Image 1 (tube, rainbow, N blue to C red):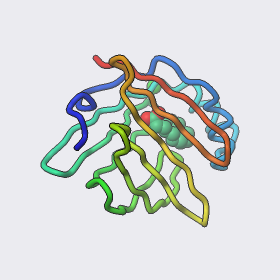
Image 2 (image 1 turned 180 degrees about the horizontal axis):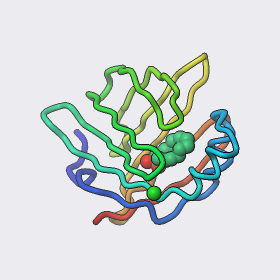
Image 3 (image 1 turned 90 degrees about the vertical axis):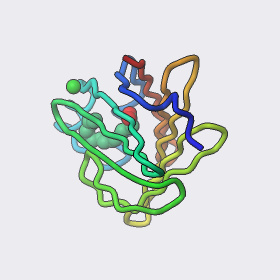
Length: 133
Ligand SMILES: CCCCCCCCCCCCCCCC(=O)O
Ligand SMILES: [Cl-]
């Protein structure tokens, strides 16, 4: 299953094309202004087969808890109510969010010791890189 190298606390060190990713989700300017200035912290823990991903920022905190392959109700940082699933493809943690007939994905894979999150929406791609502490 999920490699134990995901487990721990991660810190954003790079974000590319985040403003345009938020634009695609319908995020307003003022909210985007703060989402760009945010340097979140992502904690990934595991209790049994239930994986938890927690995001901590001064602006918004979030937390999801799921079993791989099982749909679950999620409330996103921008307050979307999504029916989401997390799958594992070649050691990549791929999260899909569906709402209002729309859909976006967050793919998280480890690269040379760093967690790389790919955000995708209608051909708009954002790349966020985290370093472990
Ligand atoms: C915690 C980030 C604050 C941004 C709030 C503005 C609304 C945008 C929400 C989009 C969520 C994108 C998160 C990508 C996954 C990650 O980088 O861990
Ligand atoms: Cl922050």
